Length: 259
Length: 259
Ligand SMILES: NCc1c[nH]c2nc(N)[nH]c(=O)c12
Ligand SMILES: NCc1c[nH]c2nc(N)[nH]c(=O)c12
Ligand SMILES: [Mg+2]
Image 1 (cartoon, each protein chain N blue to C red):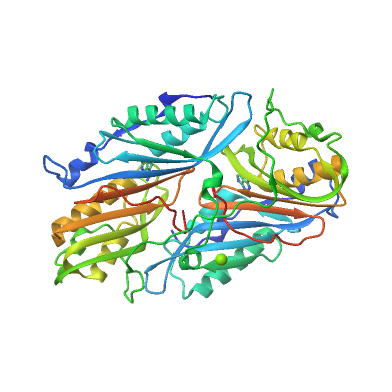
Image 2 (cartoon, rainbow over the protein chains, first blue to last red):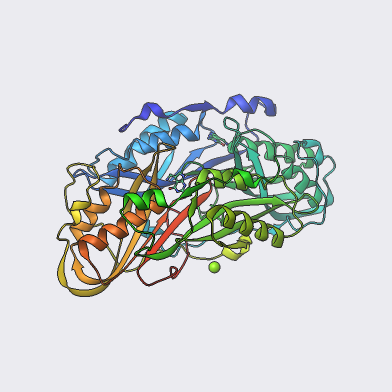
């Protein structure tokens, strides 16, 4: 099958935001950063081209794009001849923006642009090295009750232990998550227990990040908050949702060890 | 949801090797290097652990391991408590060795072992920048007929345009491939056309590398030859087959841009 934009499947963001009981105006801003590791098409003479794509979809877009549909759409490029890389980038912007309902940004980069680029970790302190027992992996937002009793602080925490189950497919999704806030100091055991409680929970990556943001806001009430997760790819695409009370986007899209 | 070695499914190497008209005495040595990006289990107190696994399966093993079955086997670790990282490595060596039919090597690495490690490209000259026209996409080993008529050389060539199809999932596989040899200098156009002709060919990653090796050996007759391909992951697992006249293992196992 060749180029087929009808393969793209929008999902309205409002569907799941409903269960978060979000007020008239969003309590966050941000974007979903996608990495497209398997971009490939043919040039006009039929010779294959390969590239990596970077896409930023605004959190305010009416729709997110369902990932399997995004994969199938990209595969439709594989046997299609295009006269230039410019055309490919242009079509991606057009088709993904039409699906999402808002202008998305797309970078199409040749593979040489990645030579010597680093694997990165996240900022601040890892909270994973704790001596606690966990036996109940059922989702429980109430694990955050009274979690922020401490002195007013600014800190950045991260964990590599985020896992949830894919809403449509049950297959596990693996991620790291970075939480930066200014407010009463958060209890790290409670936070890790809460994050681990996603382990047998069904939702999309974007929706998990919004749930973490909204739960921390309601239970811990920081003055400012950013939640950023980076998930490992499925079908050649990864999703990196960023949500913040005050920030727009992360500084870069550098990959982590499992990505 | 517990640890289950019965999920592993072997596939005999003999199926495709018989199709290549090879004897039990191989014309190559080497190994299949796998990267397990999503290795995760529970510690003795039920707290999730995450790691990256690096596995080497000897090319002399009776069997390769089917990738989906390998993924499902690894998933069975996700909700299983293990006493230590050493127990995990031991179980992996035991089960994977049993399935392959020969001792496999396993390294279980913490994610911090990858921090600030650079993405690499392949060695030598990239052959992809050619202004040629491709008229069909049918596999054709005869594209190598008379491809080695240059002076005696030792050189390393590579391409990022290797693609084949995975029949059992109906999904493309994407690879880069590095070819190092001592023999009559190879025609770059013939080599590139040959590799491009895999684009709609069904075979496993390991099998494609053996086909490339044996085709180059019979059509180009180098005195010595090494073929190393690095494929993008599927299901959290990537395969990197290495086959060589004289070398037992590749010089590195570092990830490339699309991996
Ligand atoms: N997690 C499973 C999943 C399936 N399709 C998806 N599409 C998007 N955008 N995000 C997701 O997390 C998923
Ligand atoms: N390429 C498709 C595929 C499916 N399962 C596989 N298992 C192995 N070991 N190699 C492969 O290439 C595949
Ligand atoms: Mg290293």
